[PDB]
Image 1 (cartoon, rainbow, N blue to C red):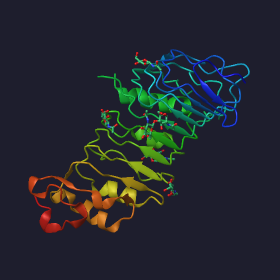
Image 2 (image 1 turned 135 degrees about the vertical axis):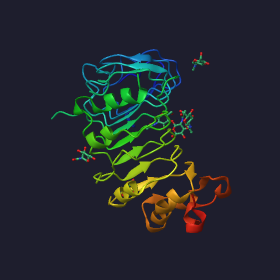
Image 3 (image 1 turned 135 degrees about the horizontal axis):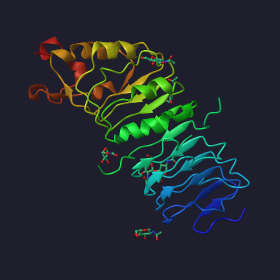
Image 4 (image 1 turned 45 degrees about the vertical axis):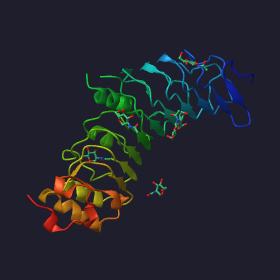
Length: 274
Ligand SMILES: *[C@@H]1O[C@H](CO)[C@@H](O[C@@H]2O[C@H](CO)[C@@H](O)[C@H](O)[C@H]2NC(C)=O)[C@H](O)[C@H]1NC(C)=O
Ligand SMILES: *[C@@H]1O[C@H](CO)[C@@H](O)[C@H](O)[C@H]1NC(C)=O
Ligand SMILES: *[C@@H]1O[C@H](CO)[C@@H](O)[C@H](O)[C@H]1NC(C)=O
Ligand SMILES: *[C@@H]1O[C@H](CO)[C@@H](O)[C@H](O)[C@H]1NC(C)=O
Ligand SMILES: *[C@@H]1O[C@H](CO)[C@@H](O)[C@H](O)[C@H]1NC(C)=O
């Protein structure tokens, strides 16, 4: 019941905030009632196994925000003994060392995992993150996954295949160039796909047909360097026909120079040349 030093607590809101206080470790005496825990703006460095494990357990803790706390290492079992944990945010931490077992018929309770801007200053980083996502099949109930701003070069096919509860996937502000060797064909449950601010030049017929087949999907494609040549014709025709693209009026050509900033929806065959 008390409230740890350097924290603010509310029994009524079941909320604990230990924010911008330069904590170097997770407080040991958190009250058992906590449902929402904010540990942002600190200097944690490393989160060890069982960093939140207590007796009695924090059995009500459902939302945990560790954003912007200079974490460079998250070790195996860091989140163990948190049977109610639904939402975890590790964004804006330079995670050089994310254990493959950081998050792991007995799946993790996690539903939402927010991992934006986790890439440390320049062993594949994307590979390390994917391993942590897929270890033990622990992330079965995961419905929302955010992986913005990570310098990722590819859309990881294994994540789409092996997290089939996913409803929301954010890969905005990465460096994706192509979707050619990834299939969206069977992603029934996928409701949102954020691909804004990548390096995509064009979408090909295969991709377009796959997306068109999904019952719930909303795709975000703004601020990519689209190339308005003859290879763009299928995508322009699709864009005119589709309802799955959000804010489709904003999509513009980056190249060639004579088409720069032209709206894709307005383009006709005579504009799309090679
Ligand atoms: C985790 O805590 C952070 C830090 O307070 C929240 O960060 C804010 O996020 C909003 C929406 O993305 C931004 O517009 C703010 O400017 C952010 N502030 C900072 C300092 O980064 C973040 O929303 C929290 N997430 C959850 C799920 O609690
Ligand atoms: C936390 O650390 C930074 C860097 O030393 C400092 O500027 C800041 O004042 C500290 N925060 C608090 C609340 O004292
Ligand atoms: C986009 O990504 C780059 C690379 O991670 C980053 O430095 C920048 O802050 C990001 N933009 C936003 C809005 O976060
Ligand atoms: C969806 O299709 C991919 C191949 O494109 C396959 O690996 C994956 O298992 C499929 N998903 C399900 C739920 O069967
Ligand atoms: C319905 O709308 C909400 C808010 O726009 C969204 O989160 C959800 O993904 C949508 N659901 C489906 C099934 O499209």
